[PDB]
Image (cartoon, coloured by chain):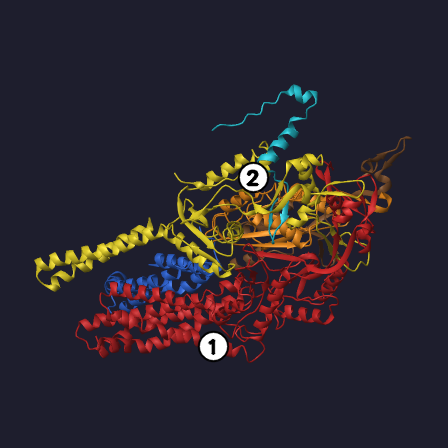
Chain colours: A yellow, B orange, C brown, D blue, E red, F cyan
Amino acid sequence: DTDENLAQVEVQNKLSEVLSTLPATVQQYGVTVSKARSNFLMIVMLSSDVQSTEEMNDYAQRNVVPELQRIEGVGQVRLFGAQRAMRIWVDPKKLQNYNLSFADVGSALSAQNIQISAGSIGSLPAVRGQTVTATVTAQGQLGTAEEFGNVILRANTDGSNIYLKDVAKVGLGMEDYSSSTRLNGVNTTGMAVMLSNSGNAMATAKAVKERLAVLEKYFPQGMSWKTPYDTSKFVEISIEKVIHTLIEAMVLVFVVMYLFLQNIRYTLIPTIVVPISLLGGFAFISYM
Amino acid sequence: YPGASAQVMEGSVLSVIERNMNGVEGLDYMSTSADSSGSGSVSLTFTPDTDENLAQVEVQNKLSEVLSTLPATVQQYGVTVSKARSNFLMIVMLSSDVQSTEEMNDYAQRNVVPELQRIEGVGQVRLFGAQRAMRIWVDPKKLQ
Amino acid sequence: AEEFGNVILRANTDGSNIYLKDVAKVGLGMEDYSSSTRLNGVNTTGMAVMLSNSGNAMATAKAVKERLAVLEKYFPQGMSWKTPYDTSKFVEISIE
Amino acid sequence: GMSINVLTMFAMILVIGIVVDDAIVVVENVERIMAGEGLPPKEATKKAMGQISGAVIGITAVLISVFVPLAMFSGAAGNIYKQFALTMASSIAFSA
Amino acid sequence: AGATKERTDATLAQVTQLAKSIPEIENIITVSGFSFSGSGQNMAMGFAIFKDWNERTASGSDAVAVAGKLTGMMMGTLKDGFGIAVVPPPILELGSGLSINLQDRNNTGHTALLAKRNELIQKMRASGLFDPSTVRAGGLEDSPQLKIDINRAAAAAQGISFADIRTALASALSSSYVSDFPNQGRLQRVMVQADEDARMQPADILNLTVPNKSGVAVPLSTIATVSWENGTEQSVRFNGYPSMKLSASPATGVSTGQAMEAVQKMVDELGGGYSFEWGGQSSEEAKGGSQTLILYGLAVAAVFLVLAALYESWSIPLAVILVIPLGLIGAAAGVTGRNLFEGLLGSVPSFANDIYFQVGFVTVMGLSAKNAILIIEFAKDLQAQGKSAVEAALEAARLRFRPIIMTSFAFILGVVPLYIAAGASSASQRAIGTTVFWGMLVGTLLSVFLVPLFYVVVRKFF
Amino acid sequence: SPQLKIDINRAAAAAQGISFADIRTALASALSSSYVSDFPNQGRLQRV
């Protein structure tokens, strides 16, 4: 008896009661709850020349969450790969060289890279006859790989500073490096949309392929979208089959009746009866 | 986020929630309003078929998954979820002579939550002002 | 507030203590100081009730005004409640 | 389950004529017959109901038919339309 | 911009003064810190509630008139503030809302997106497709902000960790939540914030002494620079993309079709990688008026069918659905006729094709069908007895004249209280008052003469 | 699968060794990465 609405959130209920006892690394990561049909509706292969797999995975995350999760029917979209992160690759030998460690570099980034909020001038409460109220900004967040390399791991007394530029190779990489997707050999990066428990196949896949059609207009060009996997085409075949077969059976039934009743007047009526009686069934179908 | 300007508020807090808010069922569209008052908002308007019960709590679902990555100041404050019609039914003006605005706001919080939120129909009561706190006003010169 | 002023910020070796009474003005204030409400000029403080998505207008407003009626009995006196804004009166006009 | 909207009352105020319409159609026809056929209150009504019953059925069915599709709209204007149409469709059904 | 509670409560004080110069207004409620656009020290809004409807019965006492008078007073006397009074929409919201949300679908600078926002605004004002006036960027204000540049070279030389700098600026400017304390049987908040004398001077920002690693108190003056630049006071992210609200309207003179059409092309013009979308208010549900041919499609189909069901032919339904425009010309001339009347003396004629005209017209179309059904059903009986078309039609019209008058004129008179209705929701009560009254009067009149003709025209052809 | 098993006698930790916590930080951050903070990348808070 399907009621994913009451169950998914009673699951989140127990997990909200649980998250604290979970390891600090896991709790920082976050444990997700999903009412997920494990079946794949369709894949959307993104192939580009100027872009790379890492780079596409960053813009994939730019058209997939705002747009491909909003679409009706789809209750989950799984991206093959990972959005890009600031990967820092320390060398343990250069660590023991300066009498350093992983705890030092970790704390270094935890200190020299923090979100700082100041406040405002002439905020409330204010003095009498104050004139201007203005917020003040300060940035304690490193944005580029170079700024991450110039972070201090240790300050020597003579004025010399040990940088992450010395002990580590810093740059933009991915969060994970496990999943490898390939269309016909070439390195492509596809997105798999799955159905929620109220998900369709023709209407949903129609929606995602004509939504991605407009999405492509705002792509960094050189970016194309192919949909090899598609179960909506199997459904289209079914409605093609119902039209063709009903035509075959109807033309057939007419023939036997005309061959027996031997006049167009006699035979024209029961073939006019069947669309009416089947349309009646069709009405009952939408009702239930 | 008391100190957060518009951009810091939008980026460090509001944008973190939004990225998890269209996995919610029947999500028609969503907007975000981050201002310099140290307050931030993100609205999720749903498709016409009304079921606020399933939606409000799927919102809380994603936000329960989110609260940890949010700034320590915000997480200590707490981020609230509400199925709110923005229209004002009525205002209840409390006027007193012996009492002051600060003092009334303390007893306002004494008759409004136990009583004016229990009442059927009302799903939100907004108090104009704030309940009283132990304010400590340090002088930075006496600090140095 | 007095107990908050006598908190130690630093204990000197001779026995002297640096208090918050010295470095700060401590007392009861508000959590925020932004919103300013005024009825006809005088400094009043009103409460705005909004409807849930299953909210009425006549029944709800009736309920809150006759609930606050009994609530006033337990008020620290000198405390009066006025309801200038009211959309239930528009409904009463309709049934009239 | 619909709370009484304003338009619903408009109906019943507009409709109030149309509920009398059938009562009028009947009462006028017996009155015509109580002058034309001019027979005792029972026999005149027999002649009335015999010539005018189906004529009343007409009025009912045509108002019922024309008023139902105003409801088949979804949305804000759809809600208001469906309300007014349903309250009418009920009132005419009970007048019929 | 750069406003504070003092100047705001000063403007609000002037507002309360002007509102209390108006006898229609009973009470006024001024609230500083909030407006429809946004929040802050510059934002404020007032609720000028009126006296009873019964007293405000004179030309210039309607909510729109006081709104216009008050706004005019403020625009003339209000110092240090843009103040305007507007009237609340009847239903849907519970002003004319037009929400475009120009989002950038490329990671370009916010400055470029708002420059393209103003570009969209400017080009839409210059164009006639987006009819002039009602042009205003929705959201909030741009304000001069302070920008503390902190070189990490100073932090590495003799400076302190960024964390301590954060603690300094945050706790000295925007208070710091430290713990909970028991107050009168309730756990309240304890908050630490720097004095007014400090966190209010722009130059004082550097004067705060951050705790160096060695227990030294060092001012920001040695490690930081303050830059008096500009910045937004409201960041809007619509649908995952940072957007901006701008306004432009085609109202009471031009259909919204062409404007909503050209605007997509407008957004296409700049960048090409920029997009827009729609939000809005009651005016978006006002759009639900081009769904009408399906209404009357289902209407005349249901009537034609039921007619062909009861009367058991196809000529009579055609003799009745022929009568539906006769009530239409009556309702339309009634609305137009009252828009004529009200415009000559002292009022602004405000009747139109609203929902009350529509629901009222549906009624009229029903009653007219009833009338046509009545006479043509009797003439249907009379054609059976070999009575000629003109004969059967005349004897029918002769026999159904009195009841038709008796019913219709009981109804036409019955909606006169709605026709003359005043007070609360009077605009609606009179809207459905006019369209029903004149729609049924002219409807009945034209029908009662042309319906016996309708039988003769139809039956002599069928 | 063939796995590696690091046996750590607490006698060594008590003699000249370090707390188990630091050993955890070492092995975890040296083998399976360590999530330290968030950084602003092209208008989006990503991971470092």
For the N terminus of chain E, give its image quadrant.
Answer: bottom right
The residue closer to the viewer here, E118 or F1, is F1
Give the residue type that dot 1 points to. Answer: Thr
* Marked residue chain, label 1: E
Residue farthest toward the top in the current orientation of the protein = F11
The residue closer to the viewer here, D16 or E37, is E37
Neighbor class of circle 2 (other Cα within 10 Å; few <14, some 14-19, many 20+) is some
In the figure, is residue A277 to the left or right of B143? left
Determine whether E132 is above or below E38 in the image.
below
For the C terminus of chain E, give its image quadrant.
Answer: bottom left
Instruction: Check if mark 1's residue and mark 2's residue have beta carbons within 8 Å.
Output: no
The residue closer to the viewer here, E337 or E10, is E10
Q: Residue at x 51, y 76 (%)?
A: E339
Mark carried by residue F29: none
Q: Quadrant of residue B137?
A: top right
Q: Residue at x 56, y 71 (%)?
A: E124
Q: Position of residue E199 (x, y in %)?
A: 79, 51
Give the residue type that dot 2 points to. Answer: Gly
In three-dimensional space, the C-alpha distance between marks 1 and 2, rounded to whole angstroms, equals 65 Å
Q: Secondary structure at mark 1?
A: helix
Determine whether E67 is above or below A87 in the image.
below
Circle 2 residue = A30
Neighbor class of circle 1 (other Cα within 10 Å; few <14, some 14-19, many 20+) is some
The residue closer to the viewer here, E96 or C60, is E96
Circle 1 residue = E336
Residue E62 at least partly seen:
no
In the figure, is residue C35 to the left or right of E284? right
Residue A150 at least partly seen:
yes
